Image (spheres, rainbow, N blue to C red):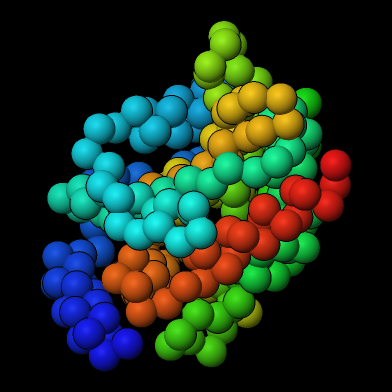
Amino acid sequence: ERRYREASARKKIRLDRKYIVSCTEVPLSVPWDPSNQVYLSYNNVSSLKMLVAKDNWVLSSEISQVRLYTLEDDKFLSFHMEMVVHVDAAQAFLLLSDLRQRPEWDKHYRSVELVQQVDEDDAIYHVTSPALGGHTKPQDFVILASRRKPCDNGDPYVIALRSVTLPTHRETPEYRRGETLCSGFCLWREGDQLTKVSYYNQATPGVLNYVTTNVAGLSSEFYTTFKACEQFLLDNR
């Protein structure tokens, strides 16, 4: 309603003012080296856990028991979605770990190609996303997906996502080369057939405007795309 439209747009303008200066000070994509595969996979998963462990997360919104947290770092904007689903965490882990089945429920992943299967729990994908507001071209990503099972009780299943570079899939004029610093899921066992599904996205300069629109409340594509995940997991029990 009017009362919310006006105050929301004010919040969006402030966030743009703060993050107009995008961010090399931090490295988005990293060279892929089969020799450093174990550390690229370790640093990938380690980064996501440290993001979860940060303390200055602030709640922005809640809709039908689906929360939305945000974190205003000095250089980049991070958000995080929380949700509880009625599926076993182990089952949700196998579904959310294969990005090839992610276009089936996420509007933001148009196509997904598997470039190289490093090992059991690590792989390199080639992702393409539709053109967001203000572009004629879709943008593509070269992402390393690393998954790890929880070590102890209470620790989460982790699926990590980081952009990398490969000499075989270099930037092409048909797509815009996007780059995400660190994203992925975190799944907790909240009980028998219960799972707290969490999506984290640390930084993606190629979609800043898109994010600040959802955080301010002027849009609801995060919630739509995230409840589609809830519906994607429930059907595979």
What residue appears at the point 52 percent right and 64 percent down from the top-left corner?
223
Q: Observer-nearest residue: 230 or 158?
A: 230
Residue 24 makes an appearance in the image: no
Estimate the x, y position of residue 100 in percent, counting from the top left: 78, 53
Is residue 180 placed above or below 207 in the rendered structure? above
Residue 160 occupies quadrant: top right
Is residue 193 placed above or below 141 in the rendered structure? above
What residue appears at the point 21 percent right and 51 percent down from the top-left corner?
72
Compared across the picture, whether 159 is left or right of 8 comes to right
Estimate the x, y position of residue 82 in percent, counting from the top left: 48, 46
Estimate the x, y position of residue 200 in percent, counting from the top left: 46, 46
Q: How many marks?
A: 0
Quadrant placement of the N terminus: bottom left
Estimate the x, y position of residue 172 in percent, counting from the top left: 60, 71
Compared across the picture, whether 201 is left or right of 229 comes to left
Q: Observer-nearest residue: 87 or 208?
A: 87
Is residue 8 placed above or below 226 in the rendered structure? below
Q: Observer-nearest residue: 47 or 68?
A: 68
Q: Residue furthest top?
A: 152
What residue appears at the point 50 percent right and 32 percent down from the top-left corner?
44
Residue 5 occupies quadrant: bottom left
Residue 17 makes an appearance in the image: yes
What residue appears at the point 26 percent right and 90 percent down from the top-left corner?
2
Quadrant placement of the C terminus: top right
